[PDB]
Amino acid sequence: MRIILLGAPGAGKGTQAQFIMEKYGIPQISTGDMLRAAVKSGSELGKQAKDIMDAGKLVTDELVIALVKERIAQEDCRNGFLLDGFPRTIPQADAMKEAGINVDYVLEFDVPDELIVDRILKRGETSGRVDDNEETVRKRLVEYHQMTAPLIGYYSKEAEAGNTKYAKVDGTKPVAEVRADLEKILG
Ligand SMILES: Nc1ncnc2c1ncn2[C@@H]1O[C@H](COP(=O)(O)OP(=O)(O)OP(=O)(O)OP(=O)(O)OP(=O)(O)OC[C@H]2O[C@@H](n3cnc4c(N)ncnc43)[C@H](O)[C@@H]2O)[C@@H](O)[C@H]1O
Protein backbone atom coordinates (compact mmCIF):
# COMPACT_ATOMS: atom_id res chain seq x y z
CA MET A 1 0.00 0.00 0.00
CA ARG A 2 1.72 3.04 -1.39
CA ILE A 3 0.09 6.44 -1.25
CA ILE A 4 1.11 9.90 -2.42
CA LEU A 5 -0.46 13.02 -0.77
CA LEU A 6 -0.45 16.08 -3.16
CA GLY A 7 -1.39 19.72 -2.46
CA ALA A 8 -0.02 23.07 -1.46
CA PRO A 9 2.05 23.47 1.67
CA GLY A 10 -0.27 23.89 4.65
CA ALA A 11 -3.11 22.10 2.88
CA GLY A 12 -3.42 19.66 5.74
CA LYS A 13 -1.46 16.72 4.36
CA GLY A 14 0.72 15.98 7.40
CA THR A 15 -2.32 16.32 9.67
CA GLN A 16 -4.15 13.60 7.72
CA ALA A 17 -1.09 11.35 7.29
CA GLN A 18 -1.30 10.10 10.89
CA PHE A 19 -4.76 8.65 10.39
CA ILE A 20 -3.69 6.96 7.17
CA MET A 21 -0.49 5.52 8.67
CA GLU A 22 -2.40 4.13 11.63
CA LYS A 23 -5.13 2.52 9.50
CA TYR A 24 -2.90 0.85 6.82
CA GLY A 25 0.08 0.12 9.06
CA ILE A 26 2.59 2.04 7.04
CA PRO A 27 5.29 4.62 7.87
CA GLN A 28 5.22 8.16 6.53
CA ILE A 29 8.10 9.37 4.27
CA SER A 30 8.14 13.14 4.78
CA THR A 31 10.97 14.78 2.87
CA GLY A 32 10.44 17.90 4.94
CA ASP A 33 10.96 15.90 8.13
CA MET A 34 13.93 13.95 6.77
CA LEU A 35 15.68 17.18 5.68
CA ARG A 36 15.07 18.96 8.98
CA ALA A 37 16.39 15.88 10.76
CA ALA A 38 19.44 15.86 8.46
CA VAL A 39 20.23 19.44 9.42
CA LYS A 40 19.83 18.80 13.13
CA SER A 41 21.96 15.70 13.21
CA GLY A 42 24.59 17.01 10.78
CA SER A 43 24.06 14.13 8.36
CA GLU A 44 26.15 14.39 5.22
CA LEU A 45 23.05 13.68 3.09
CA GLY A 46 20.79 16.68 3.67
CA LYS A 47 22.55 19.14 6.00
CA GLN A 48 22.96 21.24 2.82
CA ALA A 49 19.24 22.01 2.81
CA LYS A 50 19.26 24.37 5.78
CA ASP A 51 19.68 27.62 3.81
CA ILE A 52 17.48 26.61 0.87
CA MET A 53 14.63 25.75 3.26
CA ASP A 54 14.77 29.02 5.19
CA ALA A 55 14.63 30.82 1.82
CA GLY A 56 11.44 29.03 0.91
CA LYS A 57 13.04 27.45 -2.11
CA LEU A 58 12.91 23.86 -3.20
CA VAL A 59 15.89 21.61 -2.50
CA THR A 60 17.63 20.10 -5.49
CA ASP A 61 15.88 17.07 -7.04
CA GLU A 62 19.07 14.98 -6.85
CA LEU A 63 19.37 15.45 -3.07
CA VAL A 64 15.73 14.76 -2.21
CA ILE A 65 15.62 11.82 -4.63
CA ALA A 66 18.60 10.19 -2.91
CA LEU A 67 17.20 10.72 0.57
CA VAL A 68 13.98 9.07 -0.47
CA LYS A 69 15.61 6.15 -2.24
CA GLU A 70 17.58 5.38 0.92
CA ARG A 71 14.53 5.67 3.18
CA ILE A 72 12.34 3.36 1.17
CA ALA A 73 14.90 0.58 0.78
CA GLN A 74 14.61 -0.09 4.53
CA GLU A 75 12.66 -3.19 5.55
CA ASP A 76 9.84 -1.27 7.32
CA CYS A 77 8.76 0.07 3.87
CA ARG A 78 8.42 -3.45 2.45
CA ASN A 79 4.61 -3.47 2.76
CA GLY A 80 3.94 0.11 1.67
CA PHE A 81 4.49 3.68 2.75
CA LEU A 82 2.91 7.14 2.59
CA LEU A 83 4.83 9.82 0.59
CA ASP A 84 4.17 13.31 2.15
CA GLY A 85 5.99 16.18 0.40
CA PHE A 86 7.56 14.03 -2.37
CA PRO A 87 7.35 14.08 -5.44
CA ARG A 88 7.34 17.84 -5.48
CA THR A 89 8.44 18.32 -9.09
CA ILE A 90 7.98 16.52 -12.39
CA PRO A 91 11.63 15.25 -12.37
CA GLN A 92 11.04 13.76 -8.92
CA ALA A 93 7.94 11.94 -10.18
CA ASP A 94 9.89 10.76 -13.24
CA ALA A 95 12.56 9.27 -10.98
CA MET A 96 9.94 7.22 -9.16
CA LYS A 97 8.54 5.92 -12.46
CA GLU A 98 12.02 5.03 -13.74
CA ALA A 99 12.87 3.23 -10.47
CA GLY A 100 9.69 1.15 -10.69
CA ILE A 101 8.06 2.74 -7.65
CA ASN A 102 4.35 2.29 -8.45
CA VAL A 103 1.73 3.80 -6.16
CA ASP A 104 -1.79 2.62 -5.42
CA TYR A 105 -3.37 6.01 -4.56
CA VAL A 106 -2.65 9.67 -5.27
CA LEU A 107 -4.72 11.98 -3.06
CA GLU A 108 -4.94 15.72 -3.80
CA PHE A 109 -5.78 18.18 -1.01
CA ASP A 110 -7.40 21.26 -2.62
CA VAL A 111 -7.15 24.37 -0.39
CA PRO A 112 -7.28 28.01 -1.65
CA ASP A 113 -4.11 30.07 -1.54
CA GLU A 114 -5.64 32.63 0.85
CA LEU A 115 -6.36 29.93 3.42
CA ILE A 116 -2.81 28.51 3.38
CA VAL A 117 -1.19 31.74 4.52
CA ASP A 118 -3.39 32.01 7.59
CA ARG A 119 -3.08 28.31 8.38
CA ILE A 120 0.71 28.39 8.37
CA LEU A 121 0.92 31.59 10.43
CA LYS A 122 -1.26 30.05 13.14
CA ARG A 123 1.14 27.04 13.27
CA GLY A 124 4.41 29.01 12.70
CA GLU A 125 3.87 30.74 16.11
CA THR A 126 4.67 27.49 18.00
CA SER A 127 6.84 25.25 15.77
CA GLY A 128 9.18 28.18 15.07
CA ARG A 129 10.24 27.16 11.58
CA VAL A 130 11.77 30.01 9.61
CA ASP A 131 9.96 28.85 6.44
CA ASP A 132 6.63 29.54 8.28
CA ASN A 133 7.24 33.31 8.28
CA GLU A 134 4.71 35.22 6.21
CA GLU A 135 6.88 36.30 3.33
CA THR A 136 8.64 32.98 3.01
CA VAL A 137 5.26 31.23 2.89
CA ARG A 138 4.25 33.39 -0.07
CA LYS A 139 7.46 32.40 -1.86
CA ARG A 140 6.77 28.71 -1.19
CA LEU A 141 3.29 29.06 -2.66
CA VAL A 142 4.58 30.63 -5.85
CA GLU A 143 7.12 27.85 -6.22
CA TYR A 144 4.29 25.37 -5.52
CA HIS A 145 2.13 26.72 -8.39
CA GLN A 146 5.03 26.69 -10.88
CA MET A 147 6.83 23.44 -9.95
CA THR A 148 4.52 21.17 -7.93
CA ALA A 149 0.93 21.76 -8.98
CA PRO A 150 1.53 20.23 -12.44
CA LEU A 151 1.75 16.87 -10.57
CA ILE A 152 -2.04 17.06 -10.27
CA GLY A 153 -2.30 16.54 -14.02
CA TYR A 154 0.70 14.22 -14.14
CA TYR A 155 -0.98 11.77 -11.82
CA SER A 156 -4.49 12.36 -13.19
CA LYS A 157 -3.05 11.10 -16.48
CA GLU A 158 -1.34 8.12 -14.73
CA ALA A 159 -4.70 7.07 -13.27
CA GLU A 160 -6.35 7.34 -16.69
CA ALA A 161 -3.70 4.90 -17.96
CA GLY A 162 -4.62 2.54 -15.12
CA ASN A 163 -1.39 3.04 -13.20
CA THR A 164 -2.84 4.45 -9.96
CA LYS A 165 -6.10 5.70 -8.47
CA TYR A 166 -6.49 9.49 -8.29
CA ALA A 167 -8.84 11.39 -6.00
CA LYS A 168 -9.32 14.99 -4.83
CA VAL A 169 -10.62 16.02 -1.39
CA ASP A 170 -11.78 19.50 -0.32
CA GLY A 171 -9.24 20.42 2.35
CA THR A 172 -11.23 23.45 3.59
CA LYS A 173 -13.62 21.14 5.44
CA PRO A 174 -12.80 20.46 9.11
CA VAL A 175 -10.19 17.84 10.01
CA ALA A 176 -12.62 15.08 10.91
CA GLU A 177 -14.62 15.64 7.74
CA VAL A 178 -11.51 15.50 5.58
CA ARG A 179 -10.52 12.23 7.31
CA ALA A 180 -13.89 10.70 6.57
CA ASP A 181 -13.81 11.73 2.87
CA LEU A 182 -10.33 10.15 2.61
CA GLU A 183 -11.64 6.94 4.18
CA LYS A 184 -14.48 6.82 1.64
CA ILE A 185 -11.72 6.80 -0.99
CA LEU A 186 -9.24 4.40 0.58
CA GLY A 187 -11.55 1.93 2.25
N1 LIG B 1 10.40 16.72 -2.11
C1 LIG B 1 11.09 18.00 -1.91
N2 LIG B 1 11.75 18.45 -2.93
C2 LIG B 1 12.43 19.59 -2.80
N3 LIG B 1 12.41 20.28 -1.65
C3 LIG B 1 11.73 19.81 -0.60
C4 LIG B 1 11.07 18.68 -0.73
N4 LIG B 1 10.49 18.46 0.39
C5 LIG B 1 10.76 19.39 1.22
N5 LIG B 1 11.51 20.23 0.62
C6 LIG B 1 12.04 21.42 1.20
O1 LIG B 1 11.71 21.43 2.54
C7 LIG B 1 10.82 22.52 2.82
C8 LIG B 1 9.63 22.15 3.72
O2 LIG B 1 8.77 21.44 3.01
P1 LIG B 1 7.63 20.66 3.83
O3 LIG B 1 8.10 20.05 5.09
O4 LIG B 1 6.92 19.80 2.98
O5 LIG B 1 6.71 21.66 4.58
P2 LIG B 1 5.23 21.49 4.21
O6 LIG B 1 4.77 20.17 4.42
O7 LIG B 1 5.17 22.05 2.89
O8 LIG B 1 4.41 22.53 5.17
P3 LIG B 1 3.37 21.77 6.12
O9 LIG B 1 4.09 20.67 6.81
O10 LIG B 1 2.89 22.77 7.19
O11 LIG B 1 2.16 21.32 5.09
P4 LIG B 1 1.00 20.26 5.41
O12 LIG B 1 0.37 19.87 4.20
O13 LIG B 1 1.64 19.12 6.18
O14 LIG B 1 -0.11 21.05 6.28
P5 LIG B 1 -0.34 20.71 7.79
O15 LIG B 1 -0.82 19.35 7.86
O16 LIG B 1 0.97 20.82 8.54
O17 LIG B 1 -1.46 21.72 8.44
C9 LIG B 1 -1.21 23.06 8.34
C10 LIG B 1 -1.96 23.87 9.38
O18 LIG B 1 -3.42 23.75 9.23
C11 LIG B 1 -3.90 23.00 10.31
N6 LIG B 1 -4.94 22.22 9.64
C12 LIG B 1 -4.73 21.04 9.12
N7 LIG B 1 -5.87 20.62 8.57
C13 LIG B 1 -6.79 21.53 8.71
C14 LIG B 1 -8.12 21.61 8.33
N8 LIG B 1 -8.93 20.62 7.61
N9 LIG B 1 -8.82 22.66 8.62
C15 LIG B 1 -8.26 23.68 9.28
N10 LIG B 1 -6.98 23.61 9.66
C16 LIG B 1 -6.23 22.52 9.37
C17 LIG B 1 -2.92 22.33 10.90
O19 LIG B 1 -3.20 22.09 12.32
C18 LIG B 1 -1.72 23.21 10.73
O20 LIG B 1 -1.63 24.28 11.70
C19 LIG B 1 10.34 22.84 1.43
O21 LIG B 1 9.94 24.19 1.30
C20 LIG B 1 11.64 22.50 0.65
O22 LIG B 1 12.60 23.54 0.93
Image (cartoon, helix red, strand yellow):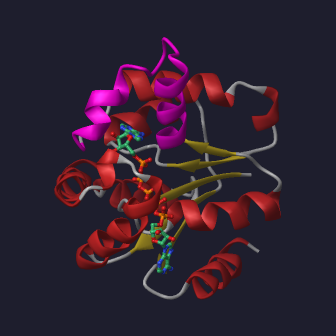
Residue 88 horizontal side relative to residue 40, left or right: left
Point out residue 136 in the picture as x, y percentages from the top left corner. 21, 52
Classify residue 95 by image quadrant: top left
- Residue 11 versus residue 84 in the image, above or below: below
The answer to whether residue 105 is left or right of residue 144 is right
* Residue 144 percent coordinates (x, y): 26, 54
Residue at 75% of width from left, 36% of height from top?
A: 77
Res. 21 image quadrant: bottom right
The stretch drawn in magenta includes residue 116: no
Q: Nearer the viewer, residue 160 or 15?
A: 15
**Quadrant, the C terminus:** bottom right
- Depth check: give the residue in front, 51 or 97: 51
Judge whether residue 33 is colored magenta.
Answer: yes
* Residue 122 x, y percent position in the rendering: 38, 71
- In terms of secondary structure, what is the magenta stretch mainly? helix
- Residue drawn at point x = 58 percent, y = 66 percent: 15
Residue 181: which quarter of the image? Answer: bottom right
**Spot occupied by residue 88 in the image (x, y as percentages of width and height):** 38, 45
Q: Looking at the image, is 144 positioned above or below residue 115?
A: above
Determine the quadrant in which ligand 1 lies.
bottom left
- Residue sitting at x 53%, y 41%: 33
Residue toward you, 157 or 46? 46
**Residue that appears at 36% across and 76% down:** 111
- Taking 185 as reference, is 29 above or below it? above
- Residue range in magenta is 31-56
Front residue of this view, candidates 31 and 42 = 42
